[PDB]
Image (cartoon, rainbow over all chains, first blue to last red; front, side, top):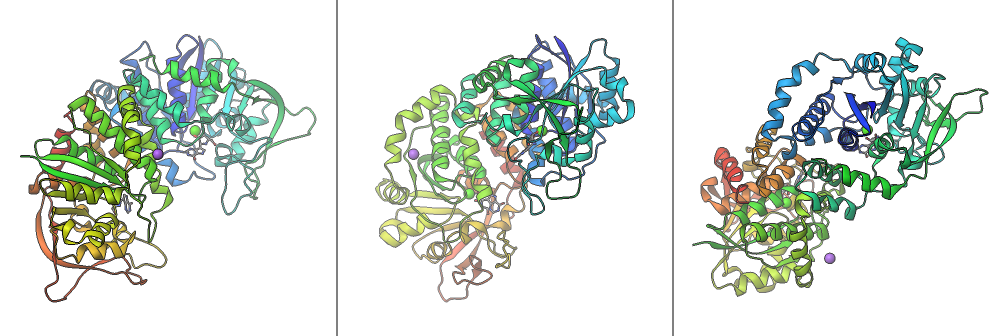
Length: 316
Length: 317
Ligand SMILES: O=c1[nH]cnc2c([C@@H]3N[C@H](CO)[C@@H](O)[C@H]3O)c[nH]c12
Ligand SMILES: O=c1[nH]cnc2c([C@@H]3N[C@H](CO)[C@@H](O)[C@H]3O)c[nH]c12
Ligand SMILES: [Ca+2]
Ligand SMILES: [Ca+2]
Ligand code: NA
């Protein structure tokens, strides 16, 4: 197993990603998580992370791990309508089973001591073996670590597997002020993304919309979780997919961390537009000589991923 | 002992909580049919969720199967698209997709597909041996269609209509550039049909307007109590729906009254509906017309009684 830290922002797919990482203990040792006030309100995202962790800890061999709220602030906030989803999950029956909330109330204070950005730096730098960071929210926290510690941090990262961007397809940030070329995780904090994508010392795998677009979440698939209601994780994952849209963005990204068979990768030099322009947050190919490479996921194995998640959701 | 009830709903989350409340209380309520309207739902999804809930309950608490119809009613003023997708979400929920339950729904779905809800409502009421209570949790289009078609032949077979809709002495919830905020959505969706219903002399009406429903908020701690009951399919179902929903229990409170009238005392008010294209289109207003029919408006509902009733009902299976 390899050490993994989940750096997430508390939306539905972030939590599916969490379940995928945590359930696959043969491949993944989940040593920490941080939650950012991006596509959630951070207190709800924090609480849902804890409730999921406690449910799993009480039902399978999943060690407890530190959970930290990130101090990162938005450059461009997510729509309020999407940010409420962690609040909904916080109230779900599956996450409010007596034995699990009792545990979470008990261990909450220890996790309240953490600040997410510092926790990420510490977990990576203090690890004996290198750490894979799975980033399913904005890149603010990885950038903070790079800015503060530089090579002391980046040399300890096995790879940064990132959900974000849109390279050779349209983005998903459609606002009166934008041209639709940017993707939301990057748009939330463009400068931090620029720091991450341009860092020569960091290995990066990028699940941009180019790959996530090709793995739709369809109703008959979601309904298959209904065949598994004796498994708590299947109630959980099925419920979250049922509440979500048509994509599995962050879950696909986490699936790759579990098993790289999920997608092939192509090296591309990726820059980020940080200017206050219609294309703010766009991830763009750059011709600059010696610009660092990012390994962009291509043609993901949709069926393999979908099977992986269904199976993983039988862990408990 | 049990009284005949038909649920006339539009497939939002509280409509389905209402359905569970009616169906789970078999001592008091014999649920003889349901219809779904293409209002605060896409009707195919509301139809499927109704079937899936009924089948789950049939297989786990012996709830008798009943006809489910889709209404052909069309909006005068349609609900926002962003609210109408919730039945689609529910249709994909694990709790509603357990194989034994879905196989039962698959077996009986085609017979239900063939109904048209408006005629179904008329037939269920008129062909019943005993009088029928109609619990209306969407727009009033279907009750109006029956009154228009059959008049006294229909209304004489109705025990009462228990209606979620309107706003009498409080503001509404229809907030548009063209409105003054005094109308409530179920009425605003089809004002003319609501007018027909509230002005009908042959008919006992109980009205849960925003006056009463505003006073029973659905809060996180209460919703989280369903987590104590995850051994019950209905607690997973109801808790999930409240967790997904907004701040109120509109239709569920309305159904609770059908189960037990101690939910609220009522106040007779002559209710007219504004149908002209004015800022308060869809408003339920007091009318001073002589000998105008009375509607019994719920006042000061028993919140704790309701909250307890629902937690208990959600332990039926
Ligand atoms: O429509 C949406 N609802 C909730 N979250 C997202 C996102 C978030 N941003 C990423 C995909 O662009 C992914 O991490 C997801 O959590 C994009 N679009 C939506
Ligand atoms: O936010 C809302 N505004 C207006 N109506 C509703 C509803 C539906 N409309 C009715 C309350 O206006 C009730 O029957 C409910 O099912 C849910 N949420 C809202
Ligand atoms: Ca995310
Ligand atoms: Ca309704
Ligand atoms: Na159909």
